[PDB]
Every structure is written in structure tokens, then in C-alpha cells.
Length: 251
Length: 277
Ligand SMILES: Cc1cccc(Nc2cc(Cl)nc(SCC(=O)O)n2)c1C
Ligand SMILES: Cc1cccc(Nc2cc(Cl)nc(SCC(=O)O)n2)c1C
Image 1: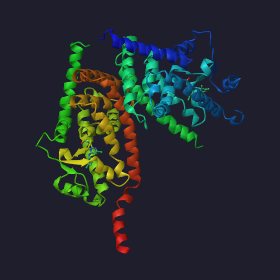
Image 2 (image 1 turned 120 degrees about the horizontal axis):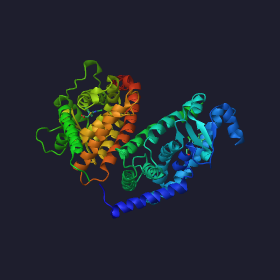
Image 3 (image 1 turned 120 degrees about the vertical axis):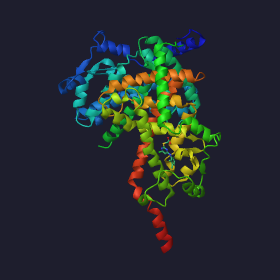
Image 4 (image 1 turned 90 degrees about the vertical axis):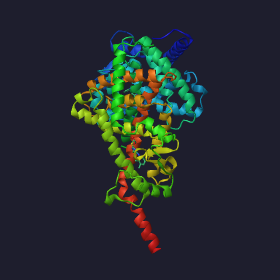
């Protein structure tokens, strides 16, 4: 049980702040994405890329223009990944305390954070069938991405695997805003000078998260613990990504 | 706020069960170790290894239990000490396996899954419990009979000098949570019953057991640490640290593996050198 007091009020105020910021930083929210994936909004009718024929109809710089469909698609992911770092960096700047940190720690926390957030928010854009691309204008199937020649055909599978289990938590934009902020303010990132001040902020964010998950998910056993376990999955996934980016890099 | 009801009583019964199993499987508890490290018990007065002189007096006055067989008997102090760690690691697996067998549900699982969970879990439990034996200054060895300093371990020739540092780094942050044996019994049982281990067939039944254990843990941490912010969350975050720590251990065991005949032939070569030149 809880009480409505000044402490619980400030954690609600903190949660509202992060959501309004999330909304300003992230154009394609989970609510928007779920609406497109379930046919509800007329606004977007994404083109479905499910095979080589629809990939060609689908597209419709100069010296990285490759014949190999696998190359063009991996360059799409790379461009959107740079865009996603901008959005996350904008979000990060609205987390109370975060700019009052050593400019050094700031770039550190972001350096290891972005890949964890990308994967977290990639789940928002995914169902069983595939993933929204180009702000909900395109939809690329899981199986088409699997069909790409090795090792590109193995690139997104682990992301799909993550998303199925993560989307079963049934988190909304309010849940995700606080979760994403908890990820960024991670004490245990290599090379940080001032750890305590990052930790004191995360303790507040973890409190805000616990309060948000209790209020927002009345029918949910250990959703806080199941969410914090996911931060372990995400580390493992980044490791597997990096190892694959460095097999692709080599050949 | 909570209620004392049948559900909360089953969770306290489950915690009591795990503690009494932990006391049975783990001869040197944190409570015993803290008592040695603070000088309270006269029972153990550990011999302190802090330099090559005390290491030599150390092997003869500690009866390590771990008798290194005749033909892996190295001159290189670094070799003998790593072989010490290796023998105590095998011993630690026996103790964890025994503990594992008492976690309700754990034996009702595919014998395959049982071996999987233990296969990845022992490395995480070893680090967890090594913290129990550590302070700022070093680590208890041979069931509290010795104490080897952090700095003496760092002083050993590369790469052996880098072997325990990460364990000290982890222990410092983990020991600041101030967990006791009750807390650790449930935390260790949570780690073993991890759904996400490569190669498990039946995930759900492991997940169902772990959800009960995470409930028992939350209740134990609330009742046992009244003055502690988000201790449950901070404990779960440690379970992420341990993955990264094990990855670093394993990579170092495989740099040692590659160069193991090469490093214990430096002494006999050092003799041939000063004999010739
Ligand atoms: C153009 C294109 C082709 C194939 C896949 C994807 N999606 C990706 C891939 C990666 Cl690695 N990262 C992202 S960022 C997801 C988001 O936060 O919107 N989006 C995109 C956007
Ligand atoms: C000879 C020596 C030197 C340094 C450390 C240790 N002890 C270790 C080493 C390792 Cl890798 N693992 C353990 S398990 C800790 C426990 O519960 O006793 N104990 C030992 C036995």
C-alpha cells in the first residue's frame, strides 16, 4: 500500500515531466506505432516489403550505392541509428540533474546507453510479423530480413526475439519514458568519474518507475523486477550486435 | 505496506527453508567470515600472506587441503596460487550444486536444464560469495585459515596480477549493500533459476519458480533492511554486473589457457640464463 504525500506527488511530477519530454523527442511513439500495426489510423498505410519484388517497388549518397539489397538495407538501419542518437540525446538533456554532470560522464552514459534505448524502442515498432520503418511509412517483414545473405540475415532476429518477450510486458509511453531514463543514468558504465551523483538520480528514477508501474499495471506480478531483468537482456544483445558489426566491418 | 496472510507466510517459510539449506551447504558463511575479518572470534587466527616471505611461511603453516599433485608443482608463485583458486572453485561447485538441490521445484526440472542453469550460474555465485570473504585489504582462503592481501595478488606477474582485482572491485560495491546470509540465500537461488540461459528447453517452469523467489526476496529485503532505498532494484542491477564480470573472467582464463606451459618455464629458463651468462 502507498500514501498520496509530498514524496509520491514529486515522483508523479517527475514522471509527467519525462513523458512530456519523450513526446517532444520521439515523433513515432508506441501508441502511434500500435495504431498503425493494428490498422486503426488511416493516417499511415505503410507499404509492406515482404520480398525482392516489394523491396524494389518499396524504395520508389551516390558512391555507397550498392547492387546487393542487403547493403542498401543495412545503410538504412545505419542512417536511422544516427537519427535515433539525436532523439535520445535530446531526451537525455530533459532528465533533471543530467546536464549538471561532468560533460565527460554525459558523453559516457550516452555512449553505452544509445544501443540499449534503440533496441528498447525498436520493440515499440515491432510485432510477430516485422518492424515499422521510415516513421511508419514502410513495414519490413521478419522473414524477409531473415532471408538476406549471411551474415546480414542474422542482424535483426535477436531484436525480434527480445521484442516478443519485452512487448509481453505491455508497457506504454509513460512506462517507457522512465525506463529509458533509468537506462541512461547507469552507474556501472566504464570510465565515469563521478558515480555517486548519477546513482542518486537513478535512485529517484527507480522510485518514479516503481510508483508508475504500480499505478499503471494493477494486474501485474513483479513487473518492476521483470522490467529490471530486461536491462540484463539488453547488455547481452548489445554485445552480440557489436560482435556482428565487427564481422560485417571486416568483410 | 504489507499484510501478514497465508501468501506472506509461505514466502517467509520459503526464505527460512533456503537459509537452513545455505547453512548446510556453505560451511563458511558471511557472519562467520565477518567475525574473522574483524578479529572477534579467537577460533580462527588466519595467517596473513602479504609478500613472498609470508607466502613461503604460508604454504607450510596452512595445510591448504588442496594438495597440488606432484607433476603440476611449479616454482612460479603465480602458478601455485592460481591452482589454489582452481581447486577451491571445483569445491565451490559441489557446495552450490548441494544448495541448488534444496530449491523447491529445481529437481522436478529436465536433468538437461538442471545442468545448464548450474553451468552458467556457478561463476555468478562464486563472485557473490567471494565478496562474503573479502574486505578492503584482501580475501579469506582455506576456510578462514589464511588471508591473502589485495596488493599481494596485484603484485603477481601479468596476467595473474589482474585475476582477482575485478572480484575486489565488485566486492567493494556489493559489500556496501550490507547483505546478510538470509538475504544472500534467496539472491543466490534467484541467480540459479535464470530463464535466459542458452540451451534451456523448458523456460516457463524455471520462470515460475524465479517469480516466487523474487517475491520471497522483495519481502526479505523489506523486512530485513528498513532503512534502505530501492535495495531490491540495486540487488537486481548487480545480477547485470555479474554477467559482464563473468565475461571478463572467462576471457582472462582463455589468455592464461593459451600461454600456461609458457609461463611456468620462465623459472627453469632464468636458471639456464644465470648459469650460462
Ligand atoms: C530504413 C530501415 C531499414 C531497416 C530497418 C530499419 N530500422 C532500424 C534499424 C536499427 Cl538498427 N535501428 C533503428 S532505430 C528504431 C527507432 O527507434 O525508430 N531502426 C530502418 C529504419
Ligand atoms: C589460494 C587462493 C588464493 C586466492 C583466492 C582463493 N579463493 C577463491 C578463489 C576462487 Cl576463483 N573462488 C573462490 S570461491 C570463494 C568461497 O566461497 O570460498 N575462492 C584461494 C583459495
